[PDB]
Length: 155
Length: 155
Image (cartoon, rainbow over all chains, first blue to last red; front, side, top):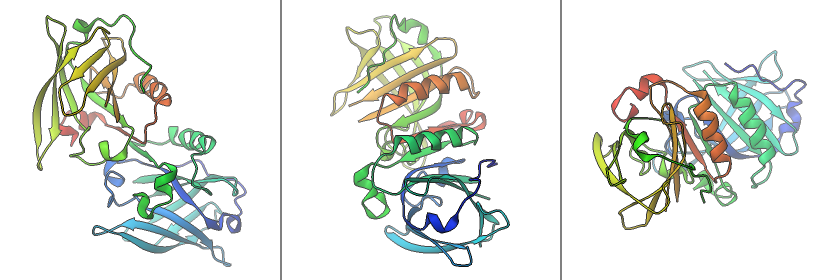
């Protein structure tokens, strides 16, 4: 499970543009294919006034790159959000400096991402990402180059 | 490119049973799918008397797990072998202790593996694997659990 949350998270400050620089998952099948279920590209985070988090992303679905808008509801823990599905799905913010990177996980089993503000490889962010994962039973990891980060569904 | 070879490699001593515990590649497409091109499961290494290396592996091809036998020809460098294809493909042995692990890469762009003798997670081997990769521009990494390592094509 995930025992890394961001202490003192200010959700309003994660607002705006992000790039899914790297992804990792507990199970290969969660990320292997273009259309793999947990292989979603974040576009924008929109905290609500009420402190919920609207997430704009892209998902490759039926041989094309589709826009998806989901809402993750706030909990009593600032760094933990709940998504509505057939399963009780949790979004955990592990760490962020707001201005460059944000690490998060979705768990039921588990997929995590390293988000960055700009379409650049941020070695410092990937370092924190790898450190946060050494805690977790991941079996697949992906990363994207600057050229892919500027394309729909990272093609 | 790969600037990690095993100094003093004794090819006769890599003979026998291996498990593709982890794989990494320069490009997501080389490993993403079951049928991805560089996603081959090593079964056995058979050095020839003449010092060539026969490799027995499995490849998921046309919705099933197929046996494949390839030969990599020795070069003047003990730790480097050449495979016959439309492209000049090179096998480089990075490191081995013969008794537990062997790391190798195939390059044209690049796929590497962490081989182990037994169907167990060897953290020491994965450590050496990650260290060897920090040199290389990998964008996908996979690992297999003991249950998968005992199945045809790691299903």
